[PDB]
Image (cartoon, coloured by chain):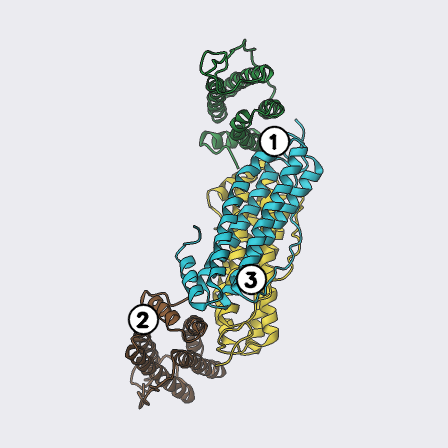
Chain colours: A brown, B cyan, C yellow, D green
Amino acid sequence: VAQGPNGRALAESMNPDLLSAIQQHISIERYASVTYLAMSIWCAERELAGFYQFFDGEAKDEQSHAVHFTQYLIARSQSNDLQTLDAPRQNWDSLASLMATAFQMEADTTSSIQSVYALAERNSDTRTTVFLDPLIEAQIQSEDQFAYLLGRVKFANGDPTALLVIDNELRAGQTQR
Amino acid sequence: VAQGPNGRALAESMNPDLLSAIQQHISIERYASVTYLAMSIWCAERELAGFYQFFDGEAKDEQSHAVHFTQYLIARSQSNDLQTLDAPRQNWDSLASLMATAFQMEADTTSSIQSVYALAERNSDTRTTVFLDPLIEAQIQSEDQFAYLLGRVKFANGDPTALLVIDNELRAGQTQR
Amino acid sequence: VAQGPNGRALAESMNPDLLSAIQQHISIERYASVTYLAMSIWCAERELAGFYQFFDGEAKDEQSHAVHFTQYLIARSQSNDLQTLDAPRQNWDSLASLMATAFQMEADTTSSIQSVYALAERNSDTRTTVFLDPLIEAQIQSEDQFAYLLGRVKFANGDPTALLVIDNELRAGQTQR
Amino acid sequence: VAQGPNGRALAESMNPDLLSAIQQHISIERYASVTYLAMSIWCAERELAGFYQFFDGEAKDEQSHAVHFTQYLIARSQSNDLQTLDAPRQNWDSLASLMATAFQMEADTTSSIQSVYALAERNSDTRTTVFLDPLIEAQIQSEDQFAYLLGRVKFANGDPTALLVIDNELRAGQTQR
């Protein structure tokens, strides 16, 4: 029995560039997490409590997603490499602009997974493509969700009354179509 | 015992033009169903989730109404004739304009039933007039309902805040007076 | 943030031929639905109540499958295009012949999904292949199911007694191995 | 306040030929009742216990229908006139032939109600047409039911095995599509 780079018994070696791509993706999701934290703070500063609660939950979820990837590397007997995390964006001129950054962050997270997926396919790493499948499925739901929230906020057209109504929807857990 | 055109035992022959009118009405209700589906999609595209849910339910109900008519033809030992279904309208400039098409579609469905009713009366088909009676009663309630939703949306006068409030009413199931 | 063809925020553009293939597949499933409705009616005309109930449920399920595809297009910010629906086949010489059309319709539905799948793979649309995966899994179960019902009806060899027994199995919900 | 022919306070006089038609219809339903009793006996003589139980219940139901009509005459302050009841048919060569008489008896019962209905319409007796409406609705269901049982028995094509299976369906209460 061979030993993997993290010391565990190795079921199948992983190509080093695929390993590197997974480690980078973990950083992307950790960065998404702290970005949702910053967005949570921005909303709380403006008394948008429903948005604050929503983004506080999203930050914790994205961190859970990141940890789920570290567990996969352990399962493949590969080394993790937790990296330096950049500071998040923290300033926006409006909730519409913040929601636009939030949607693009989710789309960019999916693009990162797709990049790992294509590399796994080129290397015929069926374990990794199968591992990623339900994660892509969740990203479809998240993109649909953030498109809904972004479009609802844009429909409000900057009217405080409409934004208070949406804020109360989010506080109640009404965050999807 | 005589055999009906669909092969079952025949309690009483049905006039061919009345049969034709019932078969056409089934197409009307199937067309109403796919029209409410298209309206459901239009609302979902604009993040009007309550309207999307309402019209999704209406599409399923109208299809149930259509099937209820096919069961009557079976019960009368008559042949069904499921027809080609036209594509629904799919574009509207506003929710007020969509709701106007929805109300007119319900009124047109009632007009179709009334046309079948008058033909049955001319042919003294008391089974058919009795069968249609509760269906007309339901159409009165549906017309009242769509007049309520249309009038509420018109009262909003295109204000996004008011439309979000109405959208949330529909999501909660508050769809009638 | 870019806007998709249906107006929502766009996570990733979809190739126009893949969009067209998904829209056509929605028509296939809508056509399967009305075909199972016609089969339901054929069985009810011959007092095969269990088969009538089975196909009535299948028609509603296939319509749900079609709607599930329209929701995916919304989620991808793509336009739906609900099309003209052909009239279904409505005449068969025997239950064995009807069940043969039913099995071929399910197999043809899977072929349609496979065609969309291959197009998505060529365009590297991992969202679509992941979305289709559980739908292919359900089609495997449906093919197994219709092969079971078709083979059971063929085993009956046109004997009314055997067909009544099978009809009662279906009425009780005994529709699979 | 005027007094009706049965001595009660009279809300509105009834035309004598309409009264006569209702009294005759009561005889029709009483005759249907004793006919289903005779059919019950025929089935019990041949150990068709499910059919025996079904027709025993039908005899009691038809008698209830007859009594419901006598109550309407009381409600209209009209005299009842319970008539001589003919002996029922009691001999059939097969269950298929018995079921044919049963279906025709139900269709003939509906024809009798339709005849009363037309007379009420000519005399503008809206109380009577409204009273008959749910009774016609029940006759549609009964015709559908007897067409189902007749067609199922004909499908059996005189095979004892198939008739035993149907007999057991009826004993379990499986009497409709």
Amino acid identity at mark 1: Thr
How far apart are labels 2 and 1 at the CA level? 59 Å
Residue on which disc 1 sits? B126
Is residue B7 visible in this depiction of the protein?
A: no
Q: Chain of mark 1?
A: B
Do marks 2 and 1 both belong to one polypeptide chain? no
Q: Which amino acid type is shown beneath numbered disc 3?
A: Ser
Residue at 68% from the left image edge and 42% from the top image edge: B20
Q: Secondary structure at mark 2?
A: helix
Image-based side of A26 in relation to D117, left or right: left
Q: Residues within 10 Å of mark 1 (few under 14, many from 20)?
A: many
Secondary structure found at label 1: helix
Foreground of the two, D147 or B73 = B73
Q: Kindly indicate whether the residues beneath marks 3 and 1 are on one polypeptide chain.
A: yes
Sort mark 2 into few (<14), some (14-19) or many (20+) by Cα contacts within 10 Å.
Answer: many
Residue where numbered disc 3 is placed: B97
**Residue D96 percent coordinates (x, y):** 60, 26
Give amino acid for label 2: Gly
Nearer the observer, B97 or C57: B97
Q: CA distance from mark 3 to mark 1?
A: 39 Å
Q: Nearer the viewer, residue A61 or B163?
A: B163
Task: Decide which of tag 3 and tag 1 comes sooner along the chain.
Answer: 3
The answer to whether residue B65 is left or right of residue A140 is right
In the rendered structure, the residue with mark 3 lies on which chain? Answer: B
Give the residue pinned by disc 2: A50
Examine the image and state in which quarter residue B161 appears: bottom left
- Residue at x 54%, y 71% (from the top left corner): C6
Measured from the top left, where is residue D112 in percent x and y? 60, 22
- Locate residue B138, reporting x and y percent: 51, 43
Q: Chain of mark 2?
A: A
C-alpha gap between disc 3 and disc 2: 32 Å
